[PDB]
Image (spheres, rainbow, N blue to C red):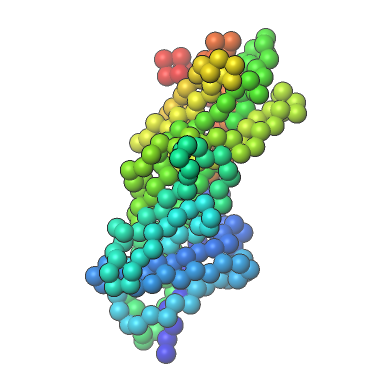
Amino acid sequence: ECRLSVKFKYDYNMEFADAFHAQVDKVELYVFDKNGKYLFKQAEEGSALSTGNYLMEVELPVGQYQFMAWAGARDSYDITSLTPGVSTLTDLKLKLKREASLIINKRMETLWYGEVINVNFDGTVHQTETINLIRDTKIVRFGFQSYTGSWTLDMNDYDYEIIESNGHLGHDNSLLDDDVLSFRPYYMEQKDPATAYVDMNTMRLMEDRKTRLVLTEKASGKRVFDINLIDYLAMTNAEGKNLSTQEYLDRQSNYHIIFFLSESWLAVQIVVNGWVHRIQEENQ
């Protein structure tokens, strides 16, 4: 007669505060048993989640379970379909959809990973479990300007890519083996050459990856800029906070980076969300 409820939170962000009700409009809870065998999933989405008091009511027999979730997953992603009593956690995988070209140029609906929890429900009390959500999709606005302003960098001369094989996530949120994808702008603006920017997005930024930002000249097809974005972000100060690289990468999901370049396409300095950082030539 007692009921088991699930609370979802999204406080693992740079505001260190829960933004679930404000940002997450779909949760899908996966339930596995004592043995790690899949039992079912349960999806809810829409206005219910926005109240500030959303709880998911989960009908479950007395017993021990593991829960995890994916939140926000809609048309951009294929999540494997599991068979009750047959499949286990390691069967659950999420893959960003791509065509043969391996180019992604759409803005994906924001994706959150719900960490795995052990749940022991004996039916004697009303109980609420909490799912903790980690943002996996990362939005970046890039600007490119002359450091001395002695030449005008024109942003429509080039193509822009973020290159990584981060499009296949396991049940533990780890990057599975996958093809390397080319993430390219979903929006570009050069109204004021000083205003000018491209908006891009990618999947998880990992401290142990070497995710690349690559610019290619339309005219020649020559690559003019090729940097390790993870490394450029690691060199920074996590926006003044006391964070490990991975924690900053997980917590922050909007990155507005201006590159101030030499005439020879060397980054002299970058500005990441307002923070100025000199790039040491040896680490360019």
Spot occupied by residue 221 in the image (x, y as percentages of width and height) = 53, 18
How many labels, in total? Answer: 0
Query: At x 46% / y 14%, what residue is drawn?
Result: 281
Q: Is residue 220 left or right of residue 187?
A: left
- Residue at x 66% of width, y 33% of height: 188
Q: Residue at x 58, y 43 (%)?
A: 106
| Rendered residue at 33%/72% (across/down) | 84
Q: Quadrant of the C terminus?
A: top left
190 sits to left or right of 45:
right
Point out the residue furthest to the left here: 35
The answer to whether any part of residue 62 appears in the image is yes
Pick the residue in front: 64 or 175.
175
Q: Position of residue 23 (x, y in %)?
A: 59, 57
- In the image, is residue 115 above or below residue 181? below
Does residue 140 appear left or right of residue 93 in this picture? right
**Nearest to the observer: residue 48 or residue 98:** 98
Q: Is residue 174 above or below residue 256?
A: below
Q: Quadrant of residue 166?
A: top left
Image quadrant occupied by the N terminus: bottom left
Where does residue 214 sit, x and y in percent of width and height? 50, 25
In this view, which residue lies farthest toward the right? 191
Question: Height in image: 142 above or below 146?
Answer: below
Which quadrant of the structure image shows residue 78?
bottom left
- The residue nearer to you, when weighing 221 against 64, is 221
Residue 94 percent coordinates (x, y): 41, 53
